[PDB]
Image (cartoon, rainbow, N blue to C red; front, side, top):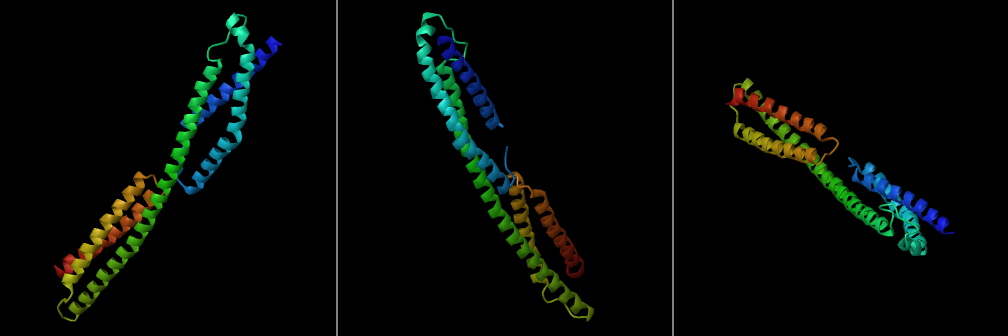
Amino acid sequence: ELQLRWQEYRELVLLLLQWMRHHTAAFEERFPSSFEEIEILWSQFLKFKEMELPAKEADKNRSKGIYQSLEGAVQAGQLKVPPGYHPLDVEKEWGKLHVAILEREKQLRSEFERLECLQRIVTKLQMEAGLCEEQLNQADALLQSDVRLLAAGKVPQRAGEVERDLDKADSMIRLLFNDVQTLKDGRHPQGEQMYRRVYRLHKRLVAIRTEYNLRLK
């Protein structure tokens, strides 16, 4: 009877408190590097929030109801509640879990918009790199027409333009290195890859500038 409600309540509150503690910690811990990852995190999150959380809400409120039946005995002294076993301590710990659910929903959305932001930059960077590469091709080809003029004892006619092209490619390469640092910071998983393709653009630039300095300067 009394001993039975009491056992139901303690059993019920013991597990409840463990499941709350477990899940509040679980959250306090997990940053996706991909959309693939975030999809899984969000699915596990919605599963918990929609499938699991409502069962435990039912258990919580059930335990409350069981407690008011026992309340005559608690106040009378016959039953004593272990610290943190009162409906009011279940509630505190439930409030916390609830806050941790809201934070995590916030973080997941913010991570998703971060990934979307890092992808705009990847497109930008890749777009700018093909342009930069074209700009290197234009400078390198102006150079050879000048170098082939010289081999037939004729003067360079585009020296001013080649120098311009390299100044432009140099500006582009510095934009690219910055895009890369913005990815690195954003913890894009390939920040270091993208750095090397830009680094390769820089070496092309240093090789073409060098040759222009010896040959036309």
